[PDB]
DNA sequence: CCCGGACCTGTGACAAATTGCCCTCAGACGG
DNA sequence: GCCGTCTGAGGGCAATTTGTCACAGGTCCGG
């Protein structure tokens, strides 16, 4: 199945995207890399890759596409829009999109890589961000270890405001997304908390391959 | 000494958002 | 040149997940 690769600058960028949008974004990076910024999406192909009906694919593409407008991307800083023209459909079952050409060098650069079958069952978009950030540190054999700062997680994944209260951070983000990765990917993941005084400051992740 | 305050934790509620499903009906084409 | 079928563009749903905050109970310090 298709092998996604992307510059680390994208793995660690600040942005907020939905799941359907992140799915499309993988195909855009794939199209661009296989060579102006103009990409294309087929309803029937999206449906087959991610196991949807054609109808639900259509719904997913259309709403994802109108939710890109006004969205911006920050590289740590410098801000860019994803799209510089609205999407449009020349043919039935076919969409044309215009990615910001200044983003191309940030897509292709110190890199992260994974096969698309690894992530296509994840549902929570914050868990997709987390799985991308672990892959950036993976060894050939399939293991790794990394320390991510809690303040940096909040900024980069643009977590919502009540998750700055740590018991809520634990309950609705950390525990749920570590559970998804262990249930929906071939990865097996564990963690431990680093503290300073009363405050918890980092999360230390270790993982191996099944 | 206590006591109140500034911190920290987990849980029960409720509100808003997202999920996979289901149904209708016209577009595009082949045979 | 018409119709039978495969698509996909629309309109919705209830059941779950995700986002928010009130309240109870831990600690340590300065007064
Ligand atoms: Ca969201
Ligand atoms: Ca959907």
Image (tube, coloured by chain):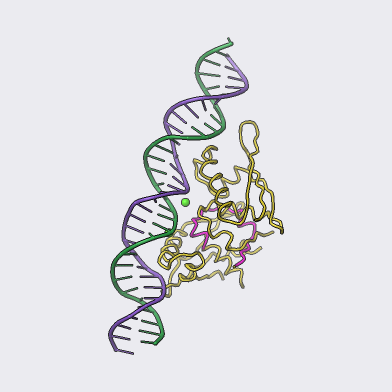
Chain colours: A yellow, B green, C purple
Q: Quadrant of residue A94?
A: bottom left
Ligand number 2: quarter of image: bottom left
Q: Where is residue A5 in the image (x, y as percent from the top left)?
A: 63, 63
Q: Report whether B18 appears left or right of A13.
A: left
| Mark count | 0
Q: Which residue is drawn at the image coordinates 63% and 56% (left, top)?
A: A9
Q: Report whether A103 appears left or right of A18.
A: right
Asked if residue A12 lies in the magenta stretch, the reply is yes
Q: Which of A85 and A193 is in front in this view?
A: A193
Q: Report whether A121 appears left or right of A63.
A: right
From this view, report whether residue C13 is shown above or below residue A39: above
Q: Report whether A192 appears left or right of A50.
A: right
Q: Position of residue A70 (x, y in %)?
A: 47, 57
Q: Which residue is drawn at the image coordinates 61% and 34% (left, top)?
A: A199
Magenta-highlighted residues: A2-23
From this view, report whether residue A85 is shown above or below residue B7: below
From this view, report whether residue A48 is shown above or below residue A14: below
The N terminus of chain A lies in which quarter of the figure? bottom right
Q: Which of A38 and A78 is in front in this view?
A: A38
Q: Position of residue C28 (x, y in %)?
A: 62, 22
Q: In which quarter of the image is residue B12?
A: top left
Q: Which residue is drawn at the image coordinates 54% and 62% (left, top)?
A: A25
């Amino acid at each position: 199945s298709p092998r996604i690769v992307q510059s680390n600058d994208l793995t660690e960028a600040a942005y907020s995207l939905s799941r359907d949008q992140k799915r499309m974004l993988y195909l855009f990076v794939d199209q661009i890399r296989k060579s102006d910024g103009i990409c294309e999406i087929h309803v029937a192909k999206y449906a087959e890759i991610f196991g949807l009906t054609s109808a639900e694919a259509s719904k997913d593409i259309r709403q994802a596409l109108k939710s890109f407008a006004g969205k911006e991307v920050v590289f740590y800083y410098e801000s860019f829009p994803w799209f510089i023209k609205p999407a449009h459909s020349p043919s039935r079952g076919l969409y044309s999109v215009h990615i910001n050409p200044y983003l191309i060098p940030f897509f292709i650069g110190r890199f992260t890589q994974f096969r698309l079958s690894e992530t296509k069952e994840i549902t929570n978009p914050y868990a997709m961000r987390l799985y991308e950030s672990l892959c950036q540190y993976r060894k050939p054999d399939g293991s790794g270890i990394v320390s991510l700062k809690i303040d940096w997680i909040i900024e980069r994944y643009q977590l919502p405001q009540s998750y700055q209260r740590m018991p809520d951070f634990r309950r609705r983000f950390l525990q749920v997304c570590v559970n998804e990765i262990n249930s929906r990917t071939p990865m097996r993941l564990s963690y431990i908390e680093k503290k300073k005084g009363r405050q918890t400051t980092h999360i230390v992740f270790s993982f191996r391959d099944i």
